[PDB]
Length: 116
Length: 116
Length: 116
Length: 116
Image (cartoon, each protein chain N blue to C red):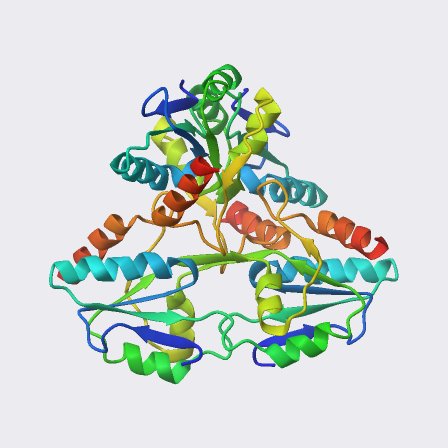
């Protein structure tokens, strides 16, 4: 698990999956759920871990001129999870009207999904 | 190099570094540069490679209920490269007025940096 | 039309609608289409136009301390167009696997939609 | 003020400025500040308001084929505020390591700026 970590309890009512920036929002929703007696854990996929230190170091160390190009990525981890493992996660929490959902909105959807 | 790949020629006038969505734009700037007799290569950092297939499979396979949470990430690879390798890339191409730059804009900045 | 502008010819085979950062990519797809004898225009929705200069000036001019908070927005203009005008645009070009589409990809989808 | 609204009290210790998705996060930071006896208001710049209903309706109503193109925008409102009004907001809360800041982080920076 240099590449993915399961945060929380092994068994849980809900297993969230995310990567990147939504980690913190989910971890708070986990704490709020405990208050209602609902358990949840988080499978967190790490982006650049473990880092290729030696490889990057030996490429850049001999370069004439290096230009870092600012970049970004948006995704549901479900697509790549399905690709690699064959599991198709049917439930998802997507962005809501041009922004990520709030913790209260995430909590809301999460319970809805639980009760579905 | 399951984690980073150097695309193009080992030696080049310019070594671009990126990850995620700007890969394709850079690769075209590489082709445009050749036209002016400028060589460039691309150190591309891969996000979820190699994927933790077995680990993810065994977490999700026993879960009661899985909820994938759509997410995103924005970054200059320079920060993490410096953290891990100690190399501080001084030249960068950032987002320009609320969007990624165009290929022509990237080409422009790239030559400016070359001639600096 | 301080708030929306129609760029190109009044009548066209395809009318693109966008706002924000995809303006430039569309305008190039327009030029590529001409090469194949396909006409296209662009209804461009402007974000902060005309700007509330006087109102903003008189709020900020008397403030003790101002803190600008960097922000963002992601959307299909179709939702708000439907809300306001009742027109439901059925065809759309969405983001493709974690990035905006390339001009060639946009061109491709555009022709597909034309021929549908 | 179909185009910008000042939410909260006219006078305040801190005047936040934002647009788009960070509206909700700021409004909560406002409530948290009250708890410490700090007042704050929010100058909120509206994106597509008032909407050009008639103009859009009459363009799209006669179109052969309409294709909505999903788009996005990232910005500090400071740039355009300076352009239009000549006020240069010196204090800012930017994105922190690849994500928007949390409410606690925003609260933190806000107080730091207050005490600077």
